[PDB]
Amino acid sequence: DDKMSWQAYVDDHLMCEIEGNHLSAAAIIGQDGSVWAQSANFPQFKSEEITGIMSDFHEPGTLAPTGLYIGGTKYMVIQGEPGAVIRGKKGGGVTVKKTNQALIIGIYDEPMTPGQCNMIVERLGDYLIDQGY
Amino acid sequence: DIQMTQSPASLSASVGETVTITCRASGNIHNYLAWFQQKQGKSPQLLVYNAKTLADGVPSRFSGSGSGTQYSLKINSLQPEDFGSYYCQHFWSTPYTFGGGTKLEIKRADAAPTVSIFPPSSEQLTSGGASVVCFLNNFYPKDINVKWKIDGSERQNGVLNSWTDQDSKDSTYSMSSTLTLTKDEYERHNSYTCEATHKTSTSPIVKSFNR
Amino acid sequence: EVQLVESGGGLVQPKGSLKLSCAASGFTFNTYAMNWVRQAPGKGLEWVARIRTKTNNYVTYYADSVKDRFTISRDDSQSMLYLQMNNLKTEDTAMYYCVRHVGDYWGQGTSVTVSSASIRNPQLYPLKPCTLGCLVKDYFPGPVTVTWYSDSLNMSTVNFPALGSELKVTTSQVTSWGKSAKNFTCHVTHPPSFNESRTILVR
Ligand SMILES: *[C@@H]1O[C@H](CO[C@@H]2O[C@@H](C)[C@@H](O)[C@@H](O)[C@@H]2O)[C@@H](O[C@@H]2O[C@H](CO)[C@@H](O)[C@H](O)[C@H]2NC(C)=O)[C@H](O)[C@H]1NC(C)=O
């Protein structure tokens, strides 16, 4: 049980200001294709996209020859933590943190350094992993 | 290591006033702040977590607010149950750090004591000792003069008195006066009385028994 | 439903060692990361340790004062969480809780006193009139956890701070208003695995 609104997580823990920079959009999407929470301008995902990321977690490195397709836009897979964190580099970028039951997706654009979007997204995932989510 | 500075260190207010405990950090903790309430002799309890999300069964009068390094907790219309020590903890990076803490003394209306006296037990009497205990409960303020009278005369030698924090329901203080003695001394005297006056117009509340 | 129980506290001689315990009940231990938090006897709370879940490879995080001296470990099979305290010093004397993540649910507590003295187990004498209470005399060191197990509704338990430092006495009161019941029972626990009971049956 959680009195914490998932929309409170994305607005206050994900879209907060770090070093004078913000995240473009962010969303909590489950291991089911359904999104648990999201921001306003975050893209409208599709079913095959989620399945492709989840398969990359079960077998690290199976999404790099094809690429990370979030919202139909393809991102080059700079896979970092095996089974924990998957990244992307369109030009912009994206980072995905795997929780026990969901995924934390944060889309960063210039001038946000990619490490900023990662520290922010990775901390929310660990917060949910240690809470059972 | 994000260290947190907490203030006011000691707060005193009447019932119904608005009070704010502010917590500041060495660096941005990104709304990963928790507020705890610890009544004396009890475990701490979660009022507000993640800066603004109140925990289950937390009164609406507790307010969480802030961003970056400046956070705060607001208690409007403070009630008797909101007494205690308030601590803040950040969860951005280990070391997860606390603050100093805030002792909130919630002033309330004047209550009246109920004095109870208890003869030395059968186990203590057997164990060659005897202690008449006297529980004065449900009183405010805590300024009370406890004295012990035996056979008409006053002895304050072995009197051990301990005061306690307020009670959640009515913010009522409590005291416990124990008079440690040997069984011989207790068996020698007959009348054992407990006297304490507190906002009773100098009419002492007395509780006595006979051995 | 959810409950966190600790044990293993007591009095330790300096340059000694200690292993505290935390028994989990009412939740899935494997999905929650557990912390240890210490409150000095008079001073405030401090964060001493944290261990993460299996998904995060059971990474153990320690505080600076205890970094080279303490050790945390968990057995999710038996649903327990431990803390090993080595090279005990006078400053380590504090009240220790086991805390789940942010601190949604805490434990009662167990205290460590790093002193050269010798433990003296308390003596529980019931006190009834010629409201009830329990008298706990001549124990060392603190604290004593006195809990009232009763058969009445609206039982009130007020605990009084310990009087005296070299040797300790404490009192406790149970106040029941307009309740028909007979069993009023106080259970006092001293840190090193001490359990004693007294009962006051009403006529
Ligand atoms: C008086 O009661 C205690 C505990 O009773 C419990 O209290 C209620 C809140 C409810 O949970 C009841 O169902 C419980 O029974 C008794 O103490 C326990 O007694 C059992 C067996 O009698 C023993 O196995 C336990 O170890 C005891 N635990 C403790 C902490 O004492 C006690 O027996 C009762 N006394 C009388 C005279 O009835």
Image (cartoon, coloured by chain):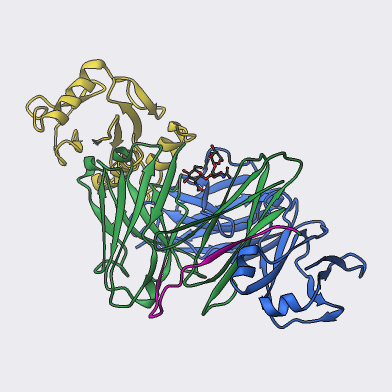
Chain colours: A yellow, B blue, C green
Q: Which of A64 and C198 is in front in this view?
A: C198
- At a point 20% along the width and 20% down the height, the residue shown is A51
Does residue B29 appear in this view? Answer: no
Range drawn in magenta: C112-129
Horizontal side of C169 relative to B24 (left or right) equals right
Query: Residue placed at 44% from the left, 39% from the top?
Result: C2
Q: Position of residue A91 (x, y in %)?
A: 19, 36
Q: Where is residue C152 in the image (x, y as percent from the top left)?
A: 66, 40
> In which quadrant will I find the C terminus of chain B?
bottom right
Residue B1 at x, y percent in the picture = 34, 63
Give the answer, above or below, for where B180 lies relative to C135: below
Quarter of the figure with residue A30: top left
- Is residue B14 among the parts visible in the rendering? yes
User: Vertically, is B192 above or below B25?
Assistant: below
Q: Toward which corner of the image does residue A28 lie, by quadrant?
A: top left
Q: Nearer the viewer, residue B105 or A28?
A: B105
Please check the rendered image and state whether residue C122 is part of the magenta-colored stretch, yes or no.
Answer: yes
Where does the image place residue C24, in percent across and percent down from the top left?
37, 44
Which residue corresponds to the image point at 66% horizontal and 64% vertical from the top-left? Answer: B121
Position of B58 with respect to B114 (left or right) is: left
Q: State left or right for residue A34 relative to residue B122.
A: left
Q: Image height check: is C140 above or below B121?
A: below
Residue closer to the observer: C118 or C196: C196
Reply yes or no: does residue A52 show up in magenta: no
